[PDB]
Amino acid sequence: MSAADFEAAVAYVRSLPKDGPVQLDNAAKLQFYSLYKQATEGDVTGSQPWAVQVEARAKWDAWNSCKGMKSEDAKAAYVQRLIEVTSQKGHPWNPA
Ligand SMILES: CC(C)(COP(=O)(O)OP(=O)(O)OC[C@@H]1O[C@H](n2cnc3c(N)ncnc32)[C@@H](O)[C@@H]1OP(=O)(O)O)[C@@H](O)C(=O)NCCC(=O)NCCS
């Protein structure tokens, strides 16, 4: 995918209204969070947090799951995941 396709995917996620036809579940939120961090900040920072800290632990595990990818590898995955999660919910989003 093109770079502007990723920047538009990030904008579409950030422009999603509260009440709308597209609502991201928590699993999809973790997926987009992991791919975004992998394509913008590189590999995961820090060690595996306390499991009691459920959110921080969940975010670190998702980010560590993508460890070893280049930024361009994760940007296409971010676009593809957005195209898929928009199709199964009745409103397909596609770039360009
Ligand atoms: C830190 C926080 C309070 C504010 O995030 P923000 O307004 O995007 O700005 P920040 O620069 O502080 O954080 C951006 C980082 O990239 C992520 N991000 C930004 N834009 C994104 C996008 N388009 N797609 C995916 N992840 C994105 C943020 O989730 C993340 O926070 P982190 O640094 O703590 O991991 C928010 O990330 C948070 O921790 N809580 C809200 C999210 C939440 O409750 N759960 C998310 C995982 S289930």
Image: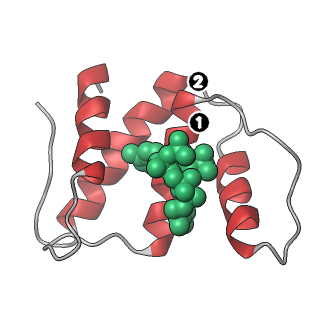
SS at circle 1: helix
Q: Who comes first in sequence, dot 1 or dot 2? A: 1
Task: Using residue 91 as the reference point, say whether residue 71 is left or right of it.
Answer: right
Residue closest to the eye, 12 or 77: 12
Residue 69 image position (x, y, % from top left) = 62, 30
Q: Which mark is residue 70?
A: 2
Task: Using residue 66 as the reference point, say whether residue 48 is left or right of it.
Answer: right
Residue 25 image position (x, y, % from top left) = 40, 74
Q: Is residue 71 above or below residue 43?
A: above
* Residue 66, quarter of the rendered image: top right
Residue 21 image position (x, y, % from top left) = 13, 73
Q: Is residue 26 above or below residue 38?
A: below
Q: Which mark is residue 38?
A: 1
Residue closest to the eye, 31 or 19: 19
Q: Is residue 85 above or below residue 40?
A: below
How dense is the environment of label 2, judged by Cα within 10 Å: few (below 14), some, or many (20 and up)? some
How dense is the environment of label 1, judged by Cα within 10 Å: few (below 14), some, or many (20 and up)? many
Query: What residue is shown at x 28% (from left), y 57% (from top)?
Result: 84
Q: Are marks 1 and 2 in contact (CB under 8 Å)?
A: no
Q: Nearer the viewer, mark 1 or mark 2?
A: 1
In the rendered structure, which amino acid carries the disc numbered 2? Lys
SS at circle 2: loop
Q: Which colour scheme appears in the figure?
A: secondary structure
Q: Is residue 92 visible?
A: yes
Q: Quadrant of the N terminus?
A: top left
